[PDB]
Amino acid sequence: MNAPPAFESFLLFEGEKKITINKDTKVPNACLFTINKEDHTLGNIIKSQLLKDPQVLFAGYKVPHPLEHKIIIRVQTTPDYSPQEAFTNAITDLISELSLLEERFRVAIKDKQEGIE
Amino acid sequence: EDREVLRVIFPTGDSKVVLPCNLLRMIWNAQKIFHINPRLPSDLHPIKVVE
Amino acid sequence: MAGILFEDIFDVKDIDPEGKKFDRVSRLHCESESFKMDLILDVNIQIYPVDLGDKFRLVIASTLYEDGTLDDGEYNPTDDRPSRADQFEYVMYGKVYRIEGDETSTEAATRLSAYVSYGGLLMRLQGDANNLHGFEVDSRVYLLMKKLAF
Amino acid sequence: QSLETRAEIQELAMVPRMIVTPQSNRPVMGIVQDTLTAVRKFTKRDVFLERGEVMNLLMFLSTWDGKVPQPAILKPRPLWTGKQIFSLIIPGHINCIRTHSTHPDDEDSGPYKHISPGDTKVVVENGELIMGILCKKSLGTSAGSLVHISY
């Protein structure tokens, strides 16, 4: 047997950290974010929120190997605006859309329905 | 003279032989890299080529 | 504004040569109203609905940003300089691979054909007035198509 | 089990060095199976990609310089063609010709009828794919192939 314990798919390891940031040297003003113990559910959404932002030149993510829980996000922005701030803002923005979605949903359920609970 | 010898080498008259160093592909690279214009006059003296 | 390599208003002779025809991309066969220049060109018919009866304006340019070069590539959506005609309905970017006429004869070098490639969408022009502008060069040339007139 | 034998394997037997076989001076390995059908399907002249799909593919490439090429169609909307994205993969300036020879086009006389871009012919220059679908004839283990020219 060689199969990992299935919980090891999502629990962070005690010697690891959740995100890691490394600069790219091929082009000016760019970054590489490492997200550990995460999957397409997270990776794909953050890609779409960043591409919505018009200051972002490039955004993409790739899961380096399927057996290996980790994703990388490359983002590149204009010199006038740090790429890190776009990422933080992109999450907060996303957090805001989901919060509004949750409030509208509960209220929509609250609409003249019965057996709602 | 080389042409006459070469007919004796290949009496069946095939044009396809195995050789090192693809000369057409190298020449083709020279045109592509030096950006040689096919229309503009070349800057090359033939005796330099022969030597 | 870009230094104009070629400029004309074209009429469509046919949309399906050989007739074989395909999706998204379609091969136009055209003729310039000067009746001294010929054109064969692919266009993305899915996003630019052409018609057989349509009369097109075609322009060819060596640049977009006023006069200086653009060989940077990297399309840069962040630019906002009104240097581009951008006024045209259909624009393509591409490279020239062949150009191509009889020159063997006495003084020949008369009547000329250019082959252009816009990322795998092919183009062919015949002329003699474009003799100063056609070059087998790196990715640089732009096709701007507009209006389809009236 | 030693540094001498590890050196001898790394230098002599290692797989990027077993590529063009002396068994018949053509590559031993070229693109196979499912990818090969997907490369055919991908290089066709009708394939177009939005800014998002190109960025995603660029992200999977390895030696990518980091400069998104200008899309072959700027207007009415950004579009990259298939051949174009493929040109980022082809090394520094590898350059083939011909190798169109699938069923398509014609059994030798049709293309001479002036070359009406019948789209089969596979032309590449300065390491940039100019036209035409890729297949077993270009990428396969055939003597004249693209993989042969890279090596």
Image (cartoon, grey):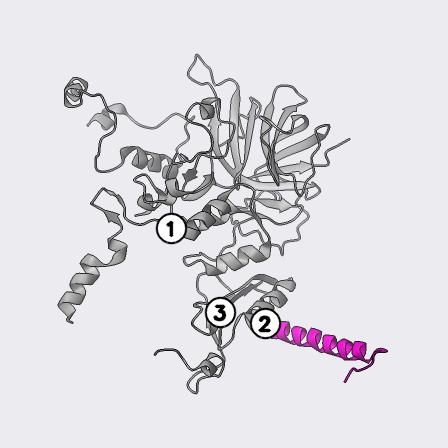
Chain under numbered label 1: D
What residue did someone put label 1 on?
A: D32
What residue did someone put label 2 on?
A: A87
Who is closer to the viewer here, C55 or C68? C55
Chain under numbered label 2: A
What residue did someone put label 3 on?
A: A72
Q: Mark yes or no: residue D75 visible.
A: yes
Q: Is residue B12 left or right of residue A68?
A: left
Disc 1 versus disc 3: distance between alpha carbons? 28 Å
Quadrant of res D25? top left
Look at the numbered disc 3 and give the secondary structure of its residue. Answer: strand
Q: Crowding at label 1, few (<14), some or many (≥20) Cα neighbours within 10 Å?
A: few
Q: Amino acid at mark 2?
A: Phe
Disc 2 versus disc 3: distance between alpha carbons? 13 Å
Q: Is residue B15 left or right of residue A22?
A: left
Q: Amino acid at mark 3?
A: Ile
Residue D122 location (% of width, % of height) = 43, 37
Residue A83 location (% of width, % of height) = 56, 69
Q: Is residue D97 left or right of residue D23?
A: right
Q: Is residue D139 magenta?
A: no
Q: Amino acid at mark 1?
A: Val
The C terminus of chain C, quarter of image: top right
Q: Nearer the viewer, mark 2 or mark 3?
A: 3
Where D128 sits versus C130, above or below? below
In the rendered structure, which segment of residues is drawn in magenta? A88-117
Q: Mark yes or no: residue A32 visible.
A: no
